[PDB]
Amino acid sequence: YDLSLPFP
Amino acid sequence: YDLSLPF
Amino acid sequence: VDREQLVQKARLAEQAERYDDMAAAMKNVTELNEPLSNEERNLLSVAYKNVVGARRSSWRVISSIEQKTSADGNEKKIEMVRAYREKIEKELEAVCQDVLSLLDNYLIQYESKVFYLKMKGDYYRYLAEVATGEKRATVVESSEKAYSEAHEISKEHMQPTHPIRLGLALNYSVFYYEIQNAPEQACHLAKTAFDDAIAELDTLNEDSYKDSTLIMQLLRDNLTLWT
Amino acid sequence: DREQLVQKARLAEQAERYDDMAAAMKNVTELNEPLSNEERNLLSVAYKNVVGARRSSWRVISSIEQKTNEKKIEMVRAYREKIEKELEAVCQDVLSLLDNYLIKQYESKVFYLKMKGDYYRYLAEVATGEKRATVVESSEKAYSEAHEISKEHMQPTHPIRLGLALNYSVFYYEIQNAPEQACHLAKTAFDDAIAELDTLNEDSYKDSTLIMQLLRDNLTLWT
Image (tube, rainbow over all chains, first blue to last red; front, side, top):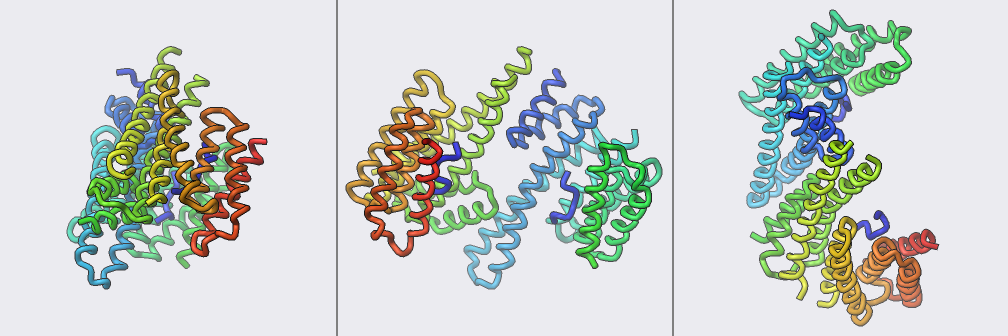
């Protein structure tokens, strides 16, 4: 986790 | 607020 | 009827930051009429403070957004904002009622009495933050009566450097500054407890020093901002 | 009306009450009218915080279960499962909104199919066995479909195409455990944006270079 886009 | 005991 | 399993459930809910489950577990533990231990006392207080704290933070944001758009002239929008504030208020009052009803009928050793009496004054103070009219006057009296009774027991059997006694004076001084709007009387409660404790600073064990001096730092931080 | 519902979502966001914000944007979505780019973000932000709060709780309880009696162990397993279906019900809620109302403009189709691949990926993080293999395929199909549409109709520097390639590469790495394919997808998306870096639109250029940095950070981490 925490590797994805932090916003839309 | 935020002046009271934090626990 | 497994009490220890409910306490361990509260410990799990705290690590998962699910304070709604944590509060329900500790409320179930309290309802067994068995005296709460020191750790279980903190578990209950941490859970319910986080539950009511989320509403206090939301209420301040909505109340700030409501009184700022009062001159906008949009009644369709101003009413929707005001209706939201009342919704958060109803949740806040219900959460406070659950703790106050639990304290008076299950909870409220002298250290536990001061701890529970301080909680009573704290949650009555949280009610006074949102209450208005005649309802605001009666929660201030119940908050003052709970703080003062805890202050009397703390002054007699507790040394001024006790973390519970120091934390009580912190919230008691905060109650007089933010609710009663009395900066001088608020400074008196914070300065007296700080002075009485710092005069006996050579009395703290190798485990309470971190806790006692932390609240003393918070007392001076409030005294600095109020002068 | 539709206006007062979006204002309630903006109110709930500032109050950090994302359950109300998601319920408000769900009502806006259920009006069957298309949503603007602002309403797309309000819906995505609301449900990301709702499912994110369940992901963060699930990771804590699951890690405790791996460490932890036969009575303290089942309670942890029963609590991990309770948080699990809460997470899965949130994912079931968005995917139903995407398939019934939002997925049918090419910029909106990749934004919604990326959401479909994201929430199917969040289901794969907690599922095992054939249940995991099923939601993995559904996440791969949604990502791959939005991948091809974003190529044909969008610029390589568009933040929606860049953000999709970021999560798509994360999908190959975190879910499929294929670092070669995860790096190749992120490097290709980074190279395509560099070759067409002149296409950086003046408004959404700080959002594009942000995701381009994130692709490099994951690329450096995975090599």
